[PDB]
Image (tube, rainbow, N blue to C red):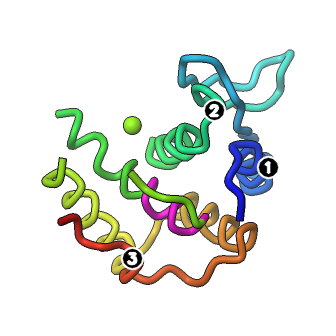
Amino acid sequence: STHHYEQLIEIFNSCFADEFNTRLIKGDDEPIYLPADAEVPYNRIVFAHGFYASAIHEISHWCIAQFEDVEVKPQALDWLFCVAAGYPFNRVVFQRRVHAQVMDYLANGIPERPARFIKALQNYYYTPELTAEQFPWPE
Ligand SMILES: [Mg+2]
């Protein structure tokens, strides 16, 4: 499969534009959240640069909502999303924390919004069910 940020916009919107009135938007240098207003009547998650990985990361942050602690769960969702999409995921100590969080999600449950997005990615890209074996321990 190819991987283009435009695909993530369509997949995200298919998942969330109705139920949560939220859409994904390609921006400039800034990640932004812009609430619905009277002119543009839907919430916007804006990601920086026309870059697949950038869009993934903002979707993860939206799903969740010293810097290391704040970033563990969003980066775990990043990893889950990347594997669900067939996209490569991207020191060692931190990624091992992220790996443990991925295992926590797989073992104990993925929250509703990222779970929905993962299922949609799998149908969009024709990928198999997630297994923990697809997430190698950082070495
Ligand atoms: Mg982040």
* Residue drawn at (27%, 65%) of the image: 99
Mark 3, ligand 1, within 8 Å: the answer is: no
Amino acid on which the number 1 mark rests in the picture: Glu
Q: Which quadrant would the C terminus be assigned to in this image?
A: bottom left
Q: Are marks 3 and 1 in contact (CB under 8 Å)?
A: no
Please tell me whether mark 3 or mark 1 is closer to you in this view. 1
- Of residues 52 and 112, the one nearer the viewer is 52
Classify 112 as above or below 30.
Answer: below
- Of residues 8 and 87, the one nearer the viewer is 87
Residue at mark 1: 10
Amino acid on which the number 2 mark rests in the picture: Ile
Classify 137 as above or below 39.
Answer: below
Residue at mark 3: 106
Give the extent of the magenta segment: 78-85
Give the image location of residue 7, x and y in percent. 75, 50
- Magenta-colored stretch includes residue 11: no
* Residue that extends furthest to the right in the rendered view of this protein: 39
Q: SS of the residue at dot 3?
A: helix
Give the image location of residue 14, x and y in percent. 79, 55
Q: Which quadrant would the N terminus be assigned to in this image?
A: bottom right
Q: SS of the residue at dot 2?
A: strand
Upstream in sequence: badge 3 or badge 1: 1
Residue at mark 2: 45
Amino acid on which the number 3 mark rests in the picture: Leu
Classify 37 as above or below 112.
Answer: above
Task: Say left or right for 45 vs 98.
Answer: right
Q: Are marks 2 and 3 in contact (CB under 8 Å)?
A: no
